[PDB]
Image (cartoon, coloured by chain):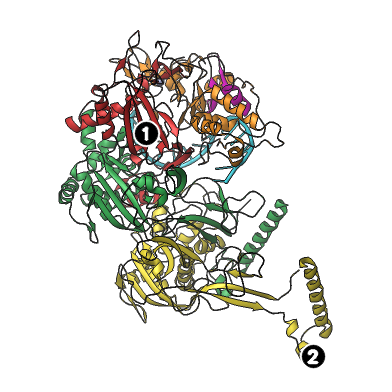
Chain colours: A orange, B red, C green, D yellow, E cyan
Amino acid sequence: MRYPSDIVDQVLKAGPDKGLLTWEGVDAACSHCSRPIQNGDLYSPSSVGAFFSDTRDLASTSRSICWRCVVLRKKPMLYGLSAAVVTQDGIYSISKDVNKAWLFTTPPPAPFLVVHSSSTMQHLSWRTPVTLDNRRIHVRYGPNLFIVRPEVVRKALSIADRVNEGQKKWVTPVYFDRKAAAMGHGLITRAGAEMLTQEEQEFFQSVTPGERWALSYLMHSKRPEPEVGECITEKVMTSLN
Amino acid sequence: VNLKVTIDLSNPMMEPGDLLHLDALLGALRVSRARAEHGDAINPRDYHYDLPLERYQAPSGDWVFKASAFKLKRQLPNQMWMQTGRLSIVEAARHRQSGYLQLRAGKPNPAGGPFKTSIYHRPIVQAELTAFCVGDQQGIEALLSECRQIGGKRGVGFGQVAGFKVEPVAETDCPWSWRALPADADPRLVTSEHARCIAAIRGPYWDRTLHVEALAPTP
Amino acid sequence: MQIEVTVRNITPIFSAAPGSNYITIDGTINPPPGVSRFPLVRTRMMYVAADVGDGVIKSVPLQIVPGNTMRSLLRRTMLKHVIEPALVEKGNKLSIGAYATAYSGNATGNPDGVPSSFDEIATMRAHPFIGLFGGGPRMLEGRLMVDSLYPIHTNAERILGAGYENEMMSGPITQVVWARRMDPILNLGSSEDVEVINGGAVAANGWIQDLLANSKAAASKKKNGRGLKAFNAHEVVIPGLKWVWRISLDRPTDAQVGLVLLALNKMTNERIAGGHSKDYGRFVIDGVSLNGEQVWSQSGITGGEQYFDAVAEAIDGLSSKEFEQFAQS
Amino acid sequence: MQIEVTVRNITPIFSAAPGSNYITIDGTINPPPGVSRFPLVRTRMMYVAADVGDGVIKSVPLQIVPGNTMRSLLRRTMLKHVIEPALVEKGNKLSIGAYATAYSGNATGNPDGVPSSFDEIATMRAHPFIGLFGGGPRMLEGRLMVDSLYPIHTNAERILGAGYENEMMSGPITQVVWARRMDPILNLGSSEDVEVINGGAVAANGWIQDLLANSKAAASKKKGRGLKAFNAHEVVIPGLKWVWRISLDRPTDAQVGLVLLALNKMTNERIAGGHSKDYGRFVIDGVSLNGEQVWSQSGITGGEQYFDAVAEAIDGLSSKEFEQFAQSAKE
DNA sequence: ACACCCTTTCTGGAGCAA
Ligand SMILES: [Zn+2]
């Protein structure tokens, strides 16, 4: 519940691969997940391929992967956590917009860990911190480390439901990009320029990029009700074995 | 002297995903000044705690500086910057025939590898940065006059500082606690914005090995 | 050290922007849905704060070249005109990790994360080229800040500061240039035109019948192979205007200043930010100021003798061993 | 390699600017609505930052030919005159995809997102034609860069630089040329004029009757389409001296020789458009190679190593590089 | 025998403003 690699044996039960070396000597942190490798725990020397391009998100330059993050670099872990929230009892999916509606509005009370892929297969699990508090959520989205406050998401959603109550067409006040890629991601629309007051506009610039990315999955004409995502920890474990 | 620093800047700044602490900036400027005196062959960690700021001490170890994270008064609406990393494929083939590049591979891969043409989009804000801290004004203005840019991606020229003003302020008028506080921080400094996180409270705030149980607000 | 290059783009500048931008048959950019629109790829614009016509600041569009594009352009000019001839002329050779580290700052040569002591960090930051950009597997911070290529324009004033009121461009700096791809089988007009083609008139008529079948299928669908006929637009920054470009050096050696100076001496053969087939980005350097001392002439850069001599002794001792030990170990 | 081609158009230049432009009968571009206006097809215009008055750079219009148009003119010149005769004099033939890739950079409108091998990239940039125009399904960088055709004018003095004060041009360089299409049937005069028409006077009277019915329908609309069409098009005036900048970053000697052969065969070529009005005809009065003038009356003088290189390469030219350049990896 | 290279293989949603 402290390091992102803890879910290897806390969220989902797993063990070392038994071809891993035993650490002898002084303390050194794992290159992935920033977990200190003590004396006696199993570790692997660093054998990343040339296709690994996340050297900028490595926690340390010790060139040693802890066994939990050896499990975390496995391909079934890589496509199993392409969109997943890992609570203290299981791994659930956030692929649907109703699942992100559940995650960023009334979050689960566990100290979870949120990963989401901005591409096909990405190293997501180890390079994000564990969110200890529901109010402050660390979301990994591709090369982006995002922080989402569900209270600010609730305030923006209440603002949007106020300015779009009674109207026939649900027009968004501020445009949000799902990929977080367009220039106008966070830019105020003309309808939102005419239908929001000044302090609401400064609020919509003042939100964090993670809240913008979350609102991108929950600001559209059909509004997703918070529905808990389907539990996928059985699918990941079966794939892992 | 219990003072407040405002920074106004010409280009819009690379928007920090996490908190941009004033003590982090002053520690980096002190590291640059230590590189100016004692050369480049130094440990940066011996000097970025030697700052013109007071230190708040938590009850069980875990001190923090009295600086605060920077607040943005956004003069402009937020935009997004695309940048790309591409290795020159044509120049690679020319160097591979000429022998200057010893590459045995015949075909590249934009998916992954040395020729991965990657795209990454990160936020951009023009703002005014306001921070609150308890420190000597002379050393803070010396470090900030040594400062020329603030924010991330400084190698691609983002967010050079047009100017700064450093003035004393009242004790009740400064929230310095809007800052990555320790988990056992004393509750008059822990507001509703502060929440529990795996976060650094000190020094290199990017060093995930130094990330601790922390109570931090959100930019 | 604050090198500052004032340039003038002889040809248009086209640094392409993301997103799906569209334009009508006239100059109306991004029309509402329900009118014929064409794919426009615009120049790199950023919204900047400016105080023009008022004491307060407003968001104005400023069409710039990114500092990433100028930084890699300076890097590739350095390599192509200085470093690759120096490594070639002594017979030094680069592995793929060292090549990727030197030419892209890329860490895939040693993606495990190379630990770096402070002594080798100091020697690598004192290297003539490695210390400028850094990065790669060791993730090193370079001595070089490369600003965006900012046009000397009234929207850029808060960026530019004082000293640019004269020769200051005003109004719009962009123009949409329309480009089309013609299907050249339609331009086959005689037996001599098609005699080079295998099949000849039969293959040409097969292409015509394929084009008519695809057009009829598209017309029936609108009530997936794309043809060669395309009509699109690209917004460029207009040629002939003046830009400034700031390259700051955070405590450099004289060899590093000489390397930036030698890059700027050979930079007019390079192109700023794309548009390559249309010769876009060709420019001349109107001035170079080294900490405010105007140092550029028609015959490159006069003066700065210590920097050029230091980079001469740096290039005389420039081997690929430093590059390979900066990348791998 | 820097090549600078100063030409002189002896016919008007008409590179039609896309858009919906109109003009009054008096000659005012884009009038306010209410007054009678005719369709004007303006020539292509590049906005250029120039020095109007003293030290006042402003964006002014200067009417040009696009670099894409001149690049395709250069491509089709060396294609029709050099590459295709070299392929015809031997047994080499191209597929329709290879012909399409050679003439327009691609065989299909959909490229494949995979790039090709470094060996094939290097050999295609070593090719005389494919190196200049590197297209194909896998997008190559062609080392030929082709600038727009700029008129030597005051408005391009920040474009031209020094060395262009001779044969100087100021003021407007464009003119609106009006064109009318008359109905042939109204120009019928007698039974001898109508004997070649099936039906003759009956068919002619039917044409007048449909024109009268359509005119009454148009009068009911105002207060199909006939053949009367009075309209306008703006051209760039003849006699101008133009600059054309051709650039080649580290070319093979055969490639710059191929550019030189194309510049030799620019005789009887039309620059932009307006074919039937003989627009785009021009005379090259200068070619400078890296600032060294190499043009005479009998084509390019000097530059012999480029010509021997391109002659050796055209002797070695085949269709195999064209076929495997156009061959899609997805296909 | 351990290093680089050349291939497959694999899980989900879906709306869109200037
Ligand atoms: Zn780990």
SS at mark 1 in the image: loop
Residue C145 drawn above or below residue B172: below
Magenta stretch bounds: A79-107
Residue D273 picture location, percent across and down: 54, 72
Q: Residues within 10 Å of mark 1 (few under 14, many from 20)?
A: some
Residue D243 drawn above or below residue D323: below
Ligand 1 closer than 8 Å to label 2 CB: no
Ligand 1 located in image quadrant? top left
Residue B206 in view of the camera = no
SS at mark 2 in the image: helix
| Residue drawn at point x = 37 percent, y = 81 percent | D298
Q: Which quadrant, please, contains the N terminus of chain D?
A: bottom left
Does residue A104 belong to the magenta stretch? yes
The residue where tag 1 is placed is B151
Does residue B37 belong to the magenta stretch? no
Residue C125 picture location, percent across and down: 24, 37
